[PDB]
Image (cartoon, rainbow, N blue to C red):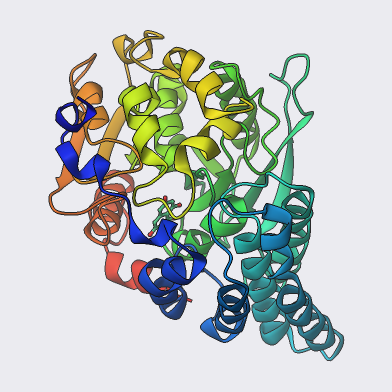
Amino acid sequence: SATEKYYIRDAITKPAVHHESYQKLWETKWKKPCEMGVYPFMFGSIKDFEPVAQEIIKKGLKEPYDWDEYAQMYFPKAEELAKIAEEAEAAGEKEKASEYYLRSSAVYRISRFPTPRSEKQKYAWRKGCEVFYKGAALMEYPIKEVRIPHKHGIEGEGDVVPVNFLLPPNASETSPVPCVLIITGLDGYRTELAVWQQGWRSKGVATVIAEIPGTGDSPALRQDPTSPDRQWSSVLDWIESQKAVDSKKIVAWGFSTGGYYALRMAHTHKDRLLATISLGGGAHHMFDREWLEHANKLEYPFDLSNTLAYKFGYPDLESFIEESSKFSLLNDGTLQKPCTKVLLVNGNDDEIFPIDDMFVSLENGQPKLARMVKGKKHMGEPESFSIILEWIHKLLGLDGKIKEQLAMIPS
Ligand SMILES: Oc1cc(O)c2c(O)cc(O)cc2c1
């Protein structure tokens, strides 16, 4: 059956305990990364989240979640942190203001995980973005929003591609810098992957952070497989206009679902990218009935397959599965085209997207760079981040000081 189909075999039939309740999500999956200040709790503090978790656990919330009831639990804490930030900014305490705005943005973020599917989650997205950019503007090296005109947009698409932008100091047309284009995931948007930007700045590298179609503020048509292609044309046209960036040194790094888009654009925009990295991406079997019919109950904190269906613009999973084959980079002929430099990295035991899709990626077109991480699930952490930074440092001729860069990630 499905138990024989994929690399992980009958692991797909074992429901993960975190789906039983929020209590199990918190105790077995979220408390630890929150304490360490890492994804999905970048910029966050256990001091903020633990009191909120305790209130959710007392209420006994669990799948199926009422996303308005769920989101509202985070709001009193998010507002408290935003009020503290405002009073700090009024007093000229810039470093403190920045911290509490970003702590507020983290609480709003988790309130609209896994993706905004209710009015209060849609509200939390807007409120989280607002406090993130207030925090970002008060960083020593401010990260700014750029509303890139979507010149390549068609009917029914948004007029702009909102991105984060950070340019290292002394970057100029005379001394231009490489750019890491970060493509975000199904749940982590530009307000989350922002955590990478100061690291890249410290190594003399510009960053642009953009969301995938049907997430954050992406203007792209959800159901149209070619919508990302138009988005990257607008984004890369804008990066080329920034003369302080070397347009011959753009590296696209796709995180999780972002990996699919990084792999896709290595083909669609080969001549405009030095390299792309897919970290925990998929390509083909991520759209399989069998995979999607099992993934709701596996390592993903909530309902992966339903969330992916919503991101692709479908009202339910069955309707998505009916048409999902058309998004395959194999089915649509993408993987037959020439590609720029591609690095594929993932944990073998991934239960969000199958390692089988790294195999499909290596079974078609030109040879690609790969590191498989045995005995690890989605993203193959922490070794994956060291592998990728080492490769990008070598590619761009940076200082190779990847431990220094990685140490800047934990909040
Ligand atoms: O350690 C990480 C860091 C991330 O940025 C992740 C992300 O964006 C998506 C995901 O599914 C897992 C992640 C794990």
